[PDB]
Image (cartoon, rainbow, N blue to C red; front, side, top):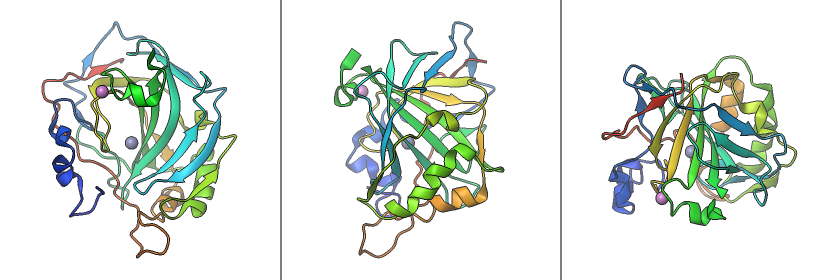
Length: 255
Ligand SMILES: [Hg+2]
Ligand SMILES: [Zn+2]
């Protein structure tokens, strides 16, 4: 699988039949159809004790991994029931500033999309959460081109080190709190992973307010390689999956 024409999203259904499931992600968020649910509690993000370990190029993105052997960085409140632990974060960007996001608002697409992945700690490990309908919690944050995001530069500088697939580098003392928008207002719906296995275990929480980043910041992303070292260079761009059918699902708003 990949994002090319011969291994693109439109071919995933052959290896991952679930790609044609009933609760697939991403979806288009129709702000007029979204239903404001008053009984929705405020989001609770506690990343003050977060501990990043490394950054890795897995061939379809770059992952910032965190230490989740303890309730260091947690996500609770909101639509969620219990504690969810931060395991890793990654992005989805385009070839141009006109595309890159997996999620869209009123059919609009952003430069990129930040996804912070959390697993329901009553399941004890990550591997077991994927086996549950409420095993994961995803924080979707949209990125627009404008002013530079200061708290994102550490990441942008290390990319040269993980240019190719398989590469990794130590990445400690990184505070994810520098990547959140001002407001925690969100939309929530039942979904899945936007990459194979495409398991339908995720509880989506897409924040309303986007974070701006500079054109030179987004450009560093696009300099990454899908390919492994010593292989023909295939730039890591357009690593996003097209919106899927909501199929009866309902998208709720906290605002
Ligand atoms: Hg699941
Ligand atoms: Zn993602």
